[PDB]
Amino acid sequence: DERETWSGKVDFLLSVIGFAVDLANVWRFPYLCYKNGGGAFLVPYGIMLAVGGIPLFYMELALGQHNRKGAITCWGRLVPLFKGIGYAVVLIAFYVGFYYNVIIAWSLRFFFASFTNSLPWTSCNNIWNTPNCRPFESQGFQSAASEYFNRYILELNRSEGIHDLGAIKWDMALCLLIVYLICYFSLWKGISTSGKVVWFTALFPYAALLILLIRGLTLPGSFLGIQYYLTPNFSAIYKAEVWADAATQVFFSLGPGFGVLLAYASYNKYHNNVYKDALLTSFINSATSFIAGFVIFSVLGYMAHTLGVRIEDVATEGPGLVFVVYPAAIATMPASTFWALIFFMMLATLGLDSSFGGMEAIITALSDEFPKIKRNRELFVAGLFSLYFVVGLASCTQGGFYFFHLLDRYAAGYSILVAVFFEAIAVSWIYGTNRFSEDIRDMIGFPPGRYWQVCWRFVAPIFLLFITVYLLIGYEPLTYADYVYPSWANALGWCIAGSSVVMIPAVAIFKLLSTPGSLRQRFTILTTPWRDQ
Amino acid sequence: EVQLVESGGGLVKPGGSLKLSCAASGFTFSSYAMSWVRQSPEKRLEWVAEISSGGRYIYYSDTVTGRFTISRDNARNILHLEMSSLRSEDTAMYYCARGEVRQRGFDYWGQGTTLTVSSAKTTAPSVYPLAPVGSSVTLGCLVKGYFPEPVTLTWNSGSLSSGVHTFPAVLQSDLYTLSSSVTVTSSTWPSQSITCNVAHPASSTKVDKKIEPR
Amino acid sequence: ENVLTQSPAIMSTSPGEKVTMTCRASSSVGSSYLHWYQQKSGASPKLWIYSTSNLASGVPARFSGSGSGTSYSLTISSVEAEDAATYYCQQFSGYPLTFGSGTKLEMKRADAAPTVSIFPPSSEQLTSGGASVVCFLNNFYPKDINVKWKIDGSERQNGVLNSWTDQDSKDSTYSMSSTLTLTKDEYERHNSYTCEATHKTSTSPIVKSFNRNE
Ligand SMILES: CC(C)CCC[C@@H](C)[C@H]1CC[C@H]2[C@@H]3CC=C4C[C@@H](O)CC[C@]4(C)[C@H]3CC[C@]12C
Ligand SMILES: CC(C)CCC[C@@H](C)[C@H]1CC[C@H]2[C@@H]3CC=C4C[C@@H](O)CC[C@]4(C)[C@H]3CC[C@]12C
Ligand SMILES: COC(=O)[C@H]1[C@@H](c2ccc(F)cc2)C[C@@H]2CC[C@H]1N2C
Ligand SMILES: [Cl-]
Ligand code: NA
Ligand code: NA
């Protein structure tokens, strides 16, 4: 009956804080505030967070602390018919590990390359440069920080597509190995250590954000970047695309449906106030994004003033923001080597605690389903990370970015949405809100308010569908720069995107032919919760 | 709006079994965790059993567990409590409460039903008129040797409300002895016919005892 | 169990005074899990103060709550007569749930001497073979009084039944009924009957005697 528990309350919180906080809080968010009406964007963001995000963030956490088991077993016990939810969710977190950990590797490679008196990405007279190189971003040209990250670090120029991955960057394979070594000795003996490793990975970014906020705000032209960041424009409120961007970002920044919030909370005490944990964590997540926004744009404004570069050419999203745009600015300011070291170290610690939970979601949900590998945690996570590293060598290739970009757009993008959708429908309609409220009451003390109950069954499916429907609208064949992916790569992507949620009906169908009885007397069996004995 | 009524209850011999019920009204019953709380004759409160809004989580006290069985019927809005192997300690006024929110406690309490677990047998009371061997004359009404509680004593069919003192029953030799005094003017009686009435339901004994001088 | 102890058990107080009842737990109790209940006589309890300090609905602002860990206290700023009841504290921290022993509020009054009335055994009781001499003691304060049975100048101290009443809600006095129960024979070998009330209101007892030869 007894499983292990967090060796301290903060361990759990820092684990959930650490997972939820991501580089997406750095480059997805401050960009969205920029393009969708400044401070006015906080209104659809705030509302979508209140009625959509936090309710879902709460739900999975509550399920974790209640059913006390991983993603596969929790949904198997909740609703036997939709046990496939547990399966679809876990291997989603398995696919992500194939491309997400290469971001941390990039951050380490830059950290190792920052040990110098003159940063290598400042000049345009290097071995890797082209005549189209300029000291900073410009319309029609390339920058020094861009060609460094592209032609030297990635050597992406030597690739003609995903069909041609080229050679293997062993300086990159080393960094990837280093990452998996760190993720290894952190999750190897479980929450006893992983609940302590997060004390660094989830706290250091805030330390770095502090001294980057100070450095960023002392720069000349820092206040100008703040204006670009938060100058109100309530015309965006009328735009549904803004409400979509607000809804999307809110949902993807809290990250339910990875079975990690489910896994993490499953190590909590049964009578732990999980309601306070959900509200606290979700806020800090959104608050972290807000803080990071100042850090970026104070530096971004500094470039648009004392370096003479258009704000349109620096207000960038994606990895380009912190691998090209931001380091270029650091290179100009005094004590550049210092800011460069702590910035890339921040980026590394921003992904580790997220990767921890992503991997932990796998290990935990598998240990509760198959008792054999629970006694074999070390030997299992050995082969798992070895598989990650082996396949991860494809990410360390010259055309490794093309493989990374394919998985990024397919593996987690759509697979999550229709998985979390079935999560909300199962709990609120199949399982039912009235007995879910009964569980939470028995745990923390009080049944959820009418607000959370309405949000869980009416607002949540609409919210998720509203996001899913617009992501369908803005779809266009996978493209990066000039390179258009061949339609077999897109087909390959949809397979990886489909191999997840294909578990929902498949397991439902397979677990429907058993056990014996009429059609009506089997839906009853497969909707009967495990705790009716 | 919110109203809780407790039925069942009565006299049960040791080892026996009785089912108490609670009829709810004025709220969505399937949204409030009910709970039984009993009160010993020395006016001491003691929690017995809690049942969830869906009746999936059950909590008992250790002095009670193994014997009692709290039950719920959210369809007809009724709360049950089935008792077995009763002992004399279980003698109390059992209340019906709805403590759905823990950090608040029981917000509404029912009227309460009385359970007496004794081996003693029901006997009828003997009512004795008490008459004086003065500004105001005081006479009495002795009700001796009945079981179990309770009884209903009033004066002149309850026309009088004060000047009257009804003393509580005191158990002795498995029998209760109750008394009551009424004070009137020296004019009023004996010119009036003041009478003591006593009503003991358990034994079907209804008496009136008009009091006379010398 | 998490036994709650309240002090003090009976508390006397004249209207206007400030009173403080305490509630200490054997184990540490969450602050938002301790609640208070008021139970007036002959009525079911009511939620009075939930979550330590938060007053319930309908509770006047004269009430307050304070405390933490293993020490809590309810406090009435200015006591009114309608606050005369018994107050139970209750911890919700863990199961099984436990109530405090409870504290009892009783108003203060200018001390009054009892109106003692003595009664001969009814002729009907003498027919059955018994003889109960009843002695009523009405309207005194404070509650503690001591009755004294004497027959023919000799102190008889066995076979009597005492019964006090609850504090009156109008004049705040008490009343007691002593019932010397005798067999008819023992009733007749003996000449006289006397009940004496030794109260603090008087230096010497209030005596009441009657005889059959008159
Ligand atoms: C912009 C950054 C700095 C802060 C983000 C604002 C967020 C954290 C705020 C704004 C509006 C807030 C919500 C307003 C409404 C409620 C109802 C309440 O019963 C639960 C909390 C909840 C859901 C709040 C949660 C926190 C909330 C979502
Ligand atoms: C603008 C930046 C620099 C502010 C830095 C924010 C830091 C200091 C804040 C944000 C989140 C906070 C943590 C949130 C979670 C907990 C759990 C709580 O039980 C102990 C405090 C602790 C551990 C907090 C410590 C302080 C904290 C780390
Ligand atoms: C690609 O998807 C993600 O990165 C999600 C999350 C995460 C989930 C799984 C994983 F293996 C690594 C990270 C990290 C943070 C929280 C949810 C969402 N991210 C914004
Ligand atoms: Cl965010
Ligand atoms: Na995030
Ligand atoms: Na992270």
Image: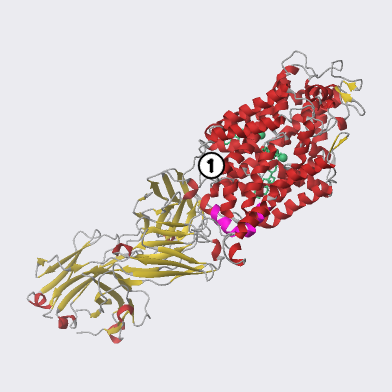
Point out residue C140 in the picture as x, y percentages from the top left corner.
29, 64
Q: Residue furthest left?
A: C189
Residue B127, placed above or below residue B173? below
| Residue in the foreground of this view, choosing between A502 and A424 | A502
Quarter of the picture holding the C terminus of chain B: bottom left
Point out residue C181 in the picture as x, y percentages from the top left corner.
17, 72
Point out residue A258 in the picture as x, y percentages from the top left corner.
65, 43
Q: Chain of mark 1?
A: A
Q: In this view of the protein, can residue A154 be seen by the observer?
A: yes
| Residue in the foreground of this view, choosing between A421 and C181 | A421
Mark 1 secondary-structure assignment? loop
Q: Which residues are magenta?
A: A422-440
**The residue under label 1 is which amino acid type?**
Tyr
Left of A26 or right of it: where is A137? right
- Residue A174 lies in quadrant: top right
**Which residue is tagged 1?**
A267
- Residue A37 lies in quadrant: top right
- At a point 64% along the width and 51% down the height, the residue shown is A84
Q: In this view of the protein, can residue A426 be seen by the observer?
A: no
